Image (cartoon, rainbow, N blue to C red; front, side, top):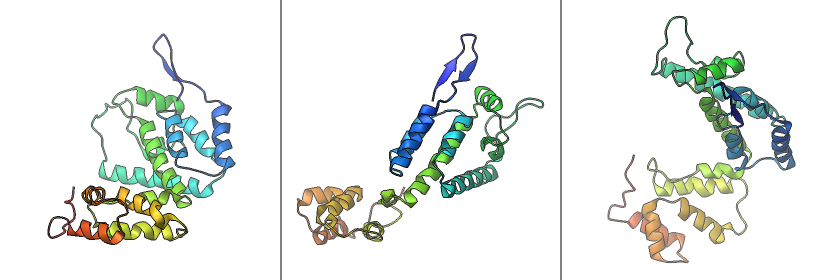
Length: 232
C-alpha cells in the first residue's frame, strides 16, 4: 500500500506497478491458490486505493466464478448493511459531501479523487476498509470452495456439542479424500486441537495414545451431567 504525503499537506497515493500485479498472477497461475494468498492480498492492498484493488482483483487470472461471487457478495453486503443501518454516526450539511453507498464503494461510478477526498474528509468514512473486508470475505469463501481450507471452517463451538462438531469434522474431510494415514494421528491431533478447551484439558491430562473411545468418554463424562460448555 504505497502512499505519499506532499510537503504542502496534500496526501496522494503512489501509482501501482506491473511488478506487484504480474507477480501476484505469476503465483496464482504457477499453482492455483492457497491460504497465504488471502492475507497477502489484504496485506498488499491494506488501505490501498479503490482503483489499484480493482486492477489487482481483475488480474486474478480469469475466475469468472470468483468475479460473480465477489460482486454479488459486495452488492448484497451493501444492500443489507444499508437496510439495517440507513445512517451512520456523523451527519452532513446541505451542499457538502454526501453519504457512502454500495454504488460509490463498488468503484464503478466512483472516482479516485472523490474516494480519497471522502476518506480524507470528515466524518471518518473509509471506503477501503469495507472494500477489502467484503472483497477478502468472498475471496476466502471462493478459494475454500476448491481448497482444503474448507475444513478450517469446521471448528468447535458453543452452538453445538463436541460430538456434533467432530461429526462434521471428519465428515467433511472424508467427503473427498481422507483415508490413508491421517487416522493414525494426523486426525487425532487435528480434532483434539480444534476440540473444545474443556475436553482438551482432559485429553492432555489423560495421556498419550488416548483412544477415541477414552477421550470421548472423558469429554462426555466431564463433571457430572456431561453438559457442554456454556454459550457466549
